[PDB]
Each structure stands twice: as C-alpha cells, then as structure tokens.
Amino acid sequence: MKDPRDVLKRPVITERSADLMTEKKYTFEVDVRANKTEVKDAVESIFGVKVDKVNIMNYKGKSKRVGRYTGMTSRRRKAIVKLTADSKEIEIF
Amino acid sequence: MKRTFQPNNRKRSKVHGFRSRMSSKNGRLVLARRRRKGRKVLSA
Amino acid sequence: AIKKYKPTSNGRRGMTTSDFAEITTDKPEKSLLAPLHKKGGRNNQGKLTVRHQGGGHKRQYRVIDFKRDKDGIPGRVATVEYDPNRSANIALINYADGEKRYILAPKGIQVGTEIMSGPEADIKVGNALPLINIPVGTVVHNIELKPGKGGQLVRSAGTSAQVLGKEGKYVLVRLNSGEVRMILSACRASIGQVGNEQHELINIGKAGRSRWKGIRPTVRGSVMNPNDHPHGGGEGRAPIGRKSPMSPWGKPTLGFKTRKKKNKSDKFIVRRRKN
RNA sequence: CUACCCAUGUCCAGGGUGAAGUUCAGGUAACACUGAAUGGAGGCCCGAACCCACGCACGUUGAAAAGUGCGGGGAUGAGGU
RNA sequence: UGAGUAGCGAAAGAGGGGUGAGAAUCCCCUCCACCGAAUGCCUAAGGUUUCCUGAGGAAGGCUCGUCCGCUCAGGGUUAGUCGGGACCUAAGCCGAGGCCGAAAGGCGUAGGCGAUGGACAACAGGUUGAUAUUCCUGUACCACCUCCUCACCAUUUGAGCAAUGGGGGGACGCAGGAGGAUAGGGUAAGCGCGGUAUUGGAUAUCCGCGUCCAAGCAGUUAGGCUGGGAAAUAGGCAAAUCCGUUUCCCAUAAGCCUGAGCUGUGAUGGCGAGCGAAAUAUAGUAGCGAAGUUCCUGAUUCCACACUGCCAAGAAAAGCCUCUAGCGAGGUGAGAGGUGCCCGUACCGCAAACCGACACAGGUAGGCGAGGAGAGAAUCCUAAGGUGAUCGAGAGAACUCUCGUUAAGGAACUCGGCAAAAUGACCCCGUAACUUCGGGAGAAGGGGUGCUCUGUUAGGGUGCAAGCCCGAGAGAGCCGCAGUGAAUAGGCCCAGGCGACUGUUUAGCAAAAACACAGGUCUCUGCGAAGCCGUAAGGCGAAGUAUAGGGGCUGACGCCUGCCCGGU
C-alpha cells in the first residue's frame, strides 16, 4: 500500500475510447483519492508500458431517482493516460 | 426588486455553517437540539 | 497666508484654503510612514461610541518625536511638510546621525537651521531642553507631564505657553487657556510657538469639506424623536422644553463641571480656566 | 434585504461656462493697476449609460405582496456600484 | 356555486415539403420582420446537470403537440503557464501564555487565517454529436535536480551560499491636456467572381476578400534619477565596503533604470474569397485554395498617476537588488537530460438553467461593445451575431386602455392649465431690472440652413509627389406648402410667502416650508481626559492635545441680537 493494483479499477469503454485508444492514450477510472503521479506508478508497474502523460478529470455524481427514492451517484475520477512510442498495449485481448 | 436570499456559498457557510456552531457553547446547543430531534441536515 | 476664492459657484462663496507657502516638498519620507485605519468612532466591541465621526479621507501617519530624547547633536531642517493628522505642519530634520525624524514645526523656521536638543541647547526656536534651564518668560510648546513620556501638552497650530516662575520642583507654566499647572521640572520641553498660525481663520465654506476631513453631520435636540434624544418632541420646532439643557444622556451641558472632584489635579493648579 | 461603518477594487458617453495661477504688452519709483493670450478649478451648466422616485395615466382576485408607459431631478461627487 | 365565465403573462409571421396515426405550434428550406451601448459574446455571483445523442410522451408546459430546460437509456468537463491552494498581507476574525469577570465567557500579546489587492512562466491555428489561451501541430517560457559534457575560480592567507538580520524597492489620491503607438473603421493598387433580360450600363459596371501571433534579437518614441565619482561617519538592537548625514571633484550629459509600439524574425508555417469529390452508418465534410500591399481616419486602451496643477496629501508583507552574522570544500556558469502536484474546467449567466411560490413585462457584477448621418454609448436604420417569444381564428359593435387627427373659438372646464398641445440642433445678431459683481442668461426677441455649379474652392491635417481626408465663407441658379423637412434633443416672463445653496428622509401614500449644511455662538475638557460602550479588563476620543475634541442653541450673506437674576 499504496499498491499499483488498487489505484486503477477498470477501463471505460465509450465512443471516446474508440478514437483515443488508437492514438496511444487510454482511459481508466482511478480511485477518488489518488493523484496523477500515483497513476504513473500503475501503468509502469502493472503493464510495463511507459507513461507519456497522465491527465486526470473528476466528475460529480448525477442525483438519479427510482420512484420516490432519490439519491446520488458515486463520484467518478477518470484518467486519460498516454504512452510512449515503441510500446504495446495489454487490453482485454 | 431585490429579495433577501442573495445566494452565497461563502457567507452562508460562515454564518450558519458547522464550525461556527461548534464555536460557541450557545452555538453547540444549536447542535444539541439538532441532534436530540435527530434531523438529517445538521446546521445549513 | 490665506487666499480666498472668487464665487464661481455657490460652493465657493465663503471658502478659504491656506496659501501653502510653508511647505516645500510633496512626496514624504517613505521610511517613516506609519499606516492608518480610520476607525469611524467605533469601539473595540464594534459599537459606535463617538457620535458623528467617520467619512474621512485616507490618512497616513508619519512618525514624530514628541520627546526629542536625543540631545546635543544639532539638527538641520531639510523640508517642512504637511500632515493630515493634525492642524500644524511637520518639519523634516536631518540630524548628523542620519536619523531623519519628522519633528513638529515651530514658526519662523525654514530650511537649514541648526536644532540641538540637549539640556545645554540654545533658546533659538526649535532647540529643546528641560524646564529647569528655561528662563522665566519664554515661548514654549511641546510640554510633557511625566519625564520622557511624549509631548502630550500643547502642540496644535499657533499655540504656545510661558514659564511664570519656578522652584527646584516644580516649574510653573501659564499654559494655553490660562491653566497654571505645576509641571515637573525635569520634563523635556521645546522652544517656540507652533507654526501655521493662521489655521483658525480658514473659512470652510462648502458643506462637504467637513465631510472631506471628515465629520458626519449632527442631528440636533428638538429634532429627534422624544425617545432618542431628551429634548425632542412637540408639534415641530417646539421650544427647548425641559429645564437644564441636556445632552443625549441625562446630564446638563451648560457649565456642569466634569472634572472629578476627588482627583489628582487639586494640587496641580494655581489658577484655572479664566472663562 | 436594508441603516451606518471599515478595507479594497471598479464605473461615470459627449459638449459647454470660464476663475485662481502664469506669460506677454502697457503701466508706477517699486508696487499697485489695466488689457491680450495662455490656463482648466468647480458639491459649476446641458445631457446619455447609471441611480433616484416628483407629475400623470395604467394596473389594482395585477405581467408584478410596489411595477409598467409617457414625462422628470442628480449625473466628478456629500456620488453610483 | 360563479362558469364553460375572467384569465391564457407585452413583442409578425407566411408559404411549400418532410416526419407521424394525428401538425398552425415539430423539423428543413425560402421570403419577411425585431434587438443591434441590446434580445450580440465571455465570465463572475449562483444553479447542480438543465449539455450532447437515441427513444418515448401519461404527467410540468397557462392550448395542442411527433417537441422541450419533461421523462427514460447511455454519453459528456483533460491544464507546470488560465482562476484558487504548495506566496504575502488589509478591515476583520481566531488566538499559547496574559488580563478581567458568580460560572459560561469578554479582550488581547507573540503567532496565524482571511482577496476584492501586491507578486506571478503560453502562444496562434486545427479539432468533435460535447472540452480548450488544456487534446493535437509548431514554437516557446518557468522553477528544481543531475546518471552526462564542457567553461571559470579557489582549497579556510576561502570559491561561493549568502538571512526569518539591516537597507532599498515594490508603494499607490484626484482633476486636465498635449504627444507617441496599437487596437478598430473606410478609399486607391491587387486577386478570385462576374456582365446581368425591367429603360439604359465591357462599362471609372457589380459581388466578395485583402492576413497573423506569445519568445527571441536589434535599436526606438518617450518617461524618469536629481545629477555621477571619491572621502569620512555619535545612526540604522549585533555587524557591515548597504542606506542615511557631511566635504571636495566632474556636471551643457556622460552613466543607470524603465518602457506603448516598429522590424526581420517566429513562418519554405496557416488562414483566406471560392471551388464544396467519392457518396458516408450520404455530416455532405475532407480535399484544393489566388491576391493578401499602400493610403486616410482613430479611442472610451496603452506608454502612464508619466507630466502639470490641486488640495481633502493619497494600504501593508513577501516575490526582487544589495550589505554584513553564520556557514563552506568543491562550487558558479553554460549546453544535453530528466521532474513538475491538488482543486476549478460541461451548460444558463439580462435568462425559460438565479433572486423573485411560476419558464412571472421586475432585480443581477465586470470585460468586449461595429457602419451611415452624427459631438456622443444620443436617436433612427442596418452588418457581426441572436431572435419569431410557445392559444389562436374572424368579425370590426357598446365600453376601457393605448395612440393619431380635428373645423371656429381658445382656459370659458377645473380647487388648480391636471393633462395634453407647445419650445427645442448648430451658426449669428441681440439680451433688461437686480446683484454677493461670478451672474441672471440657452435671459428676453429675432435671422440663416435642402440641392447644383463656381469647386481636386479659401485655408488647414497628412503625405516626396500622387493621393486622400477636414473644410469656413460667399456669388450665381434650382425646386418644393415646408429645407436641423424624419427620430431624439429647453416653453417662457412678471410678482409674491418659505428655505441660502448641490444633497438627505418617511424602503411599500407624505422629497416638503422637514433634516443636513458651512458660518455664528454658549459650555465642558490639561490629556490614565471631557463624554463614551463596557460588571470590569480593553478601546473609541487619538499614534489628536484648548487654532483640538465632546455637548447644546441657531442656521449662507447684510443690518442687528432691546429689557428682567424675582422664580427655577
């Protein structure tokens, strides 16, 4: 702790993930309290493919509703992360 | 014309907010009656 | 001197500003400006305990020896400058130490005059020395009370004092407005009546110069509601009804003496308040 | 919200009136004094943004729990924000 | 119940097609119309997804409704340089110790927080159905550190770091006006269009455009400095080669510090009028892309609170430059090469997304804010842009409101010229009583203006000329009822009462003869203060000192302010 593995959770597969993944940049959610340089700790040590850049957004939650019962989505914090040239990718495959 | 809730993030949170009512002993009685009643929104 | 304004509008029809001949330079010493906050008649609580102050222009204090603790080394008046914190002006002095000190300006001085401040010093206007060495009958200002405290006594523009005749302890002083106080003898004092003598004849003229200074306006006695002020009432412009005129507190303000009767100044007066 | 204060920023389209002060020509013995040009100060003058709230009409279970339409006062200051 | 009644919340749509079961209200196109110193854009206060797509449509939409800011289902905000925190401080707040007080607490030192301030490194394009001085494409810049390379010192007879220590500097008001430059706008050169069917125009005819950074170099309008050097110091807690004080030398500018902007650079880049292919999960984009200059006008910006003047005399600490104390053995510099965090980034921000119970003719900082006429942000009409304001149809009555005409008479109406009508822009003539000598006074009362020509007028600004602009003044002549033909621009003039005046007040009936006001006074107060708020501590008064504060009375100016101390 803080390990590389628990920092990331998933890749986020949207229409944005179609065009960005062909340009050596990849989407990942990160935990709520994990900074930019903890993300470079992951991809170097989990994936072995060296980071070009880390760019981190965060979102607030949409307060959805079901019936009478209204409540708020958990807050999300994604990360567009770029890699070097001459370096592969270790996605779903 | 002008009405009385000219909204502020700062001035609302400083007059009425939390640590302002953990400040004084009379201000914490406001945080006692907000607890023995058992409201959800403790002081706004 | 005092100029007078030609009535170009109705703001001007009485107003006078002084000639500003005594002053030499505008931009003061940067290294003795002390900053100020206009307080506005407020208290340390926050209540406004002084009526009708506030409104003024941005003042900025300049540090003044009202003591002249340093001694013997002659001064050499560089410039005489203007200070919004009081009536009179201030003369900048370059001592031979380099201790550039704003020190209150008596009349008759210009650039270049020697000003010592020892007990050995002269009776040239400006020189300062304790009251034992002062001879009977000189024009003195900047008097203190306790030795070395600071010149609480006389300071304002165009005022002075005397020395009537003294002992070892104390030195009698006919102060301004006639009070003869047995002022202590080793009290440091300085010599001369205070410059800018024509401050009184300055006709203010237009209303807002008392707001420029500033002073908030005052609301009189039979104007406020009979709640708020103990003269007010009537069906408008009623006579000043109740016996013993009365402040906005219940105390008469025609001649009702306000000195403590049991007070330290029962010994320290030979003659008081000629009225 | 509003009354007052304090600290710090910000706003005031345009054009007029012309003083103090100066310079020059004249003037006395020096002053005084007088006229030209220069000069732009002023809770000055007009008038818009802005602020106010005197008329009138309307509206009055209103578009509006205080406004709207024509007009109006202040508009470099004791100013508005 | 009233009652299918009041109301449907200012403000032009119309026509064709399409969608669908259904269309005036949905979409597209084409005509027309409105704001255009706002109804435009950009971004705060706030709001918390209202943004985009794909479906629905019961409910909220003041009516329908295939539609929505409604419902669902997904998608949506990328920052070392932008705002804010790893910087500092203002009023204020909190406050170890401390001081007062039955308690709780009140205040407050050292300290620290707290921008609306000070300091501060990035820019021009592209880009999507959604984000941009973030992604990306080119340049840059900022700080830190060295696995590296070189350059230069010195080895405590010491390179350098040099401070929370000392200085300096940051560092500041308002008014006015030159200059100088840029934004911005418009002719002549050019380059792509084009020759028009309604008379005439291959013709000085028409349409459109005409560019561009931050960093870098180089100098510059111009601004300061008070001049610069040497020498000595009763100072600056301690120190100082720093600053301040004093003595000489040189003073026509040598020397410094700062600059708006110009110029090749930046760029053999990338926009650009327009050509808009393949058809593509038919956005129709990609792609292709000529000239791209001179001239004139020009600020409400900048140089710059710089200059001049005026008084009412105009924030503080660090970033930054120095000088010591102390470190100190390997350091300074250059290039290569690394590191660079947290939050904020969607969308509305004069609105249908906020404050108004409402998608309510209201209220909401600041920065951009064009053309013709014009002084101007006036006012009108238009480009840039945005908008058709979400019940309409069709009669043309009473009556209400909003307006516009009215013959003849004009205040007879009325408490009252309430109200309307009227006057108004420049230029010129001319202008009284009265006065505090400034005014009054835009007093009053009058005359001129449209166009053509003489005439690239006279003469100025600018330019070398060419060329534009800016143009009084006049003579001839034209036409109209009308010449500031429209819109916006004062109605005056006597005589009175009150109040000097500009101002302020009863937010939401009363702006006034009320209050303020300068001036006048009477009085108290010698400073641990008179009065204050405090139970007191503390603080105002005040880094004030009887030419100053507090209290009262009266209210510019002029003439004055007569009599009674019995009462109280």
Image (cartoon, coloured by chain):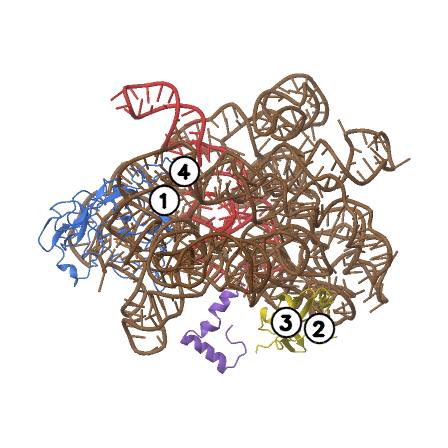
Chain colours: A yellow, B purple, C blue, D red, E brown
Q: Residue at x 35, y 54 (%)?
A: C36
Q: CA distance from mark 4 to mark 1?
A: 31 Å
Q: Would residue C113 be seen by someone viewing this image from the given angle?
A: yes
Nearer to us of marks 4 and 1 is 1
Q: CA distance from mark 3 to mark 2?
A: 12 Å
Quadrant the N terminus of chain C occupies: top left
Q: Are marks 3 and 4 in contact (CB under 8 Å)?
A: no
Nearer to us of marks 4 and 2 is 2
**Residue where numbered disc 1 is placed:** C27
In this orientation, which residue lies closer to the viewer: C48 or C145? Answer: C145
Q: Chain of mark 2?
A: A
Residue C49, by quadrant, is bottom left
Q: Which mark is residue A90?
A: 2
Vertical order, C235 against B27 (above or below): above
In this orientation, which residue lies closer to the viewer: E530 or E564? Answer: E530
Q: Residue at x 10, y 56 (%)?
A: C169
Q: Amino acid at mark 3?
A: Glu
- Give the image location of residue E237, x and y in percent: 28, 58
Residue C236, by quadrant, is bottom left
Decide if residue E187 is on the left or right side of residue E514: right
Q: Amino acid at mark 2?
A: Ile
| Tag 4 secondary structure | loop
Nearer to us of marks 1 and 3 is 3
- Give the image location of residue C255, x and y in percent: 21, 55
**Residue where numbered disc 3 is placed:** A44
Q: Are marks 3 and 2 in contact (CB under 8 Å)?
A: no
